[PDB]
Length: 184
Ligand SMILES: OC[C@H]1O[C@@H](O)[C@H](O)[C@@H](O)[C@H]1O
Ligand SMILES: [Ca+2]
Ligand SMILES: [Ca+2]
Ligand SMILES: [Ca+2]
Ligand SMILES: [Ca+2]
Ligand SMILES: [Ca+2]
Ligand SMILES: [Ca+2]
Ligand SMILES: [Ca+2]
Image 1 (tube, helix red, strand yellow):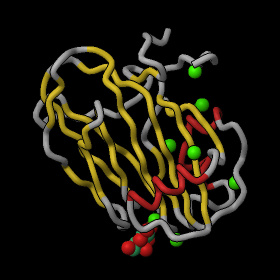
Image 2 (cartoon, helix red, strand yellow):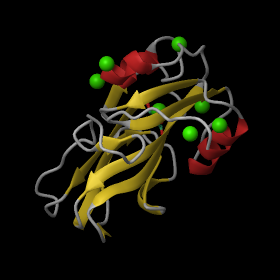
Image 3 (cartoon, helix red, strand yellow):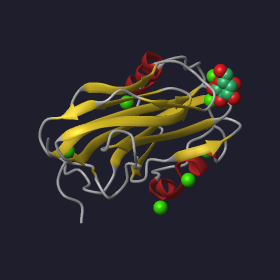
């Protein structure tokens, strides 16, 4: 547009809290669409939690975000339910990949507009090995994530494999870009 966006080795993060129930992806997306973010942050190391007693309460969000919490724009007030919306880019070579995500509650990850990892409901801590997807051309791929907590425990760690599920890595500053330019 007319405003420069910060270039960092991470995704652009937004946190939203609510006192309504989050049951599914559409509920969290409606929350995101309903207001300005309760806080913004840089999501440079996307391995959050685990903790207890509601992500949206007290300092639980800070604890959940860990290393990334130092970039919070503000300390949100309490809510019962809450979640994050992350957007930016991830450097991937052409090839085949799959996510394996540990989470409480649900989430959705999309790459180049296509969902590649989805849990459309609340759940206690579970790890799902998602189906494989292909990247046609090497470079920075567009990626967005949503995750939420309806209450209770909370964790979010979406790991990626490039080698058919033999090894997995966290998405972090090695490969993330907020704008699709290279972070130095
Ligand atoms: O489905 C029930 C589960 O819901 C999760 O949101 C919560 O973190 C768990 O502790 C358990 O209550
Ligand atoms: Ca801009
Ligand atoms: Ca919004
Ligand atoms: Ca707080
Ligand atoms: Ca941590
Ligand atoms: Ca930090
Ligand atoms: Ca709730
Ligand atoms: Ca929960």
